[PDB]
Amino acid sequence: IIGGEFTTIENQPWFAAIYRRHRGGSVTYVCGGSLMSPCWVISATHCFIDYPKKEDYIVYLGRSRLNSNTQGEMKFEVENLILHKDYSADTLAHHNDIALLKIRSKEGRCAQPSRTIQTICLPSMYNDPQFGTSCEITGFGKEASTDYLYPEQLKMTVVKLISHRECQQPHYYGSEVTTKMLCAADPQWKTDSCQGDSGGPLVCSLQGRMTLTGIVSWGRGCALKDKPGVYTRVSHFLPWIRSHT
Amino acid sequence: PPEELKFQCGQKT
Ligand SMILES: Cc1cc(I)c(O)c(C(=O)Nc2ccc(C(=N)N)c(Cl)c2)c1
């Protein structure tokens, strides 16, 4: 996240950190995700597409730091890794960029609630906040586009949703943005999601609940003027989510 | 009653 503040998992208890094992010994961060129900985390298919080997990923809940442990964190293996079959990537956009990971611990259980682990709500079919709503994004992604490392502390920031009309202006993303995407930016193009934030949540209040309105998907640069962050529009995938969970 | 019921989506504690 470019801008924002550092936070702790208590402020985003549904955030999931996904890592990959290289049996040479290292475990590297891949993407973020969000806990939907005790056994399911949702992220982005582009995070897994290149290495769909579920056995090589580890999912952690209750984590405030990237490589050090947080007291209360829970570690899970991926029992099922569902990627969207119509996932496509083009010159910028990723279409149908949503993925589901069914998690299981070594004891064979799913997540348990704690002050650091909570689920986030799903919107109702095709229901979104209106553009102008301020939503927050969280993640361990880059703080500057030129960095090659990720922060160790979790960060969060606020962005506002903008209209498709505005995001589809030729000088923004044109028709790269579809109705199955949402665009969010900071009025001053100062804070935004960046590399490493993929898979994470765009949370907005909807009907009184903190709802998972988007999944960090793609963007040109990070915090670039007229280059919003594009998120998968969760509200438009509810049938898909329900069919697999 | 079973742990799961304690999840309240959207709540921070
Ligand atoms: C190779 C790679 C890997 C990961 I994981 C990414 O998140 C990205 C990436 O470009 N993420 C990325 C970068 C910028 C933005 C933005 N808001 N402008 C967004 Cl949504 C996502 C790239």
Image: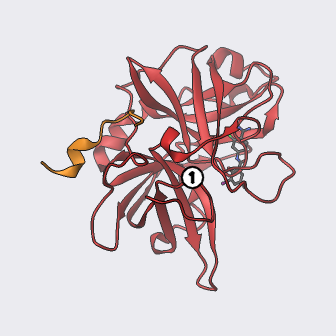
Chain colours: A red, B orange
Q: Nearer the viewer, residue A92 or A99?
A: A99
SS under mark 1? loop
Q: Say which residue appears at 66% left-offset and 52% top-offset.
A: A153
On the image, the x and y values in percent for residue A169 come to 75, 19
The quadrant of the rendering that contains the N terminus of chain A is top right
Q: Nearer the viewer, residue A195 or A67?
A: A67
Q: Say which residue appears at 28% left-offset and 72% top-offset.
A: A107
Q: Nearer the viewer, residue A188 or A99?
A: A188
Mark 1 residue's CB less than 8 Å from ligand 1: no
On the image, the x and y values in percent for residue A207 come to 38, 17
**Residue A93 visible in image:** no
What kind of residue is marked 1?
Answer: Ser
Local packing at callout 1 (Cα closer than 10 Å; few below 14, some 14-19, many 20+) is: many
On the image, the x and y values in percent for residue A165 come to 66, 15
Q: Say which residue appears at 34% left-offset and 68% top-offset.
A: A105
Quarter of image, res A75: bottom left
Which residue in the rendered view is the most extreme toward the left?
B1
Quarter of image, res A220: top right
Q: Nearer the viewer, residue A239 or A143?
A: A143
Q: Say which residue appears at 29% left-offset and 49% top-offset.
A: A245
Q: Please give left or right for residue B5 compared with residue B10 in the image.
A: left
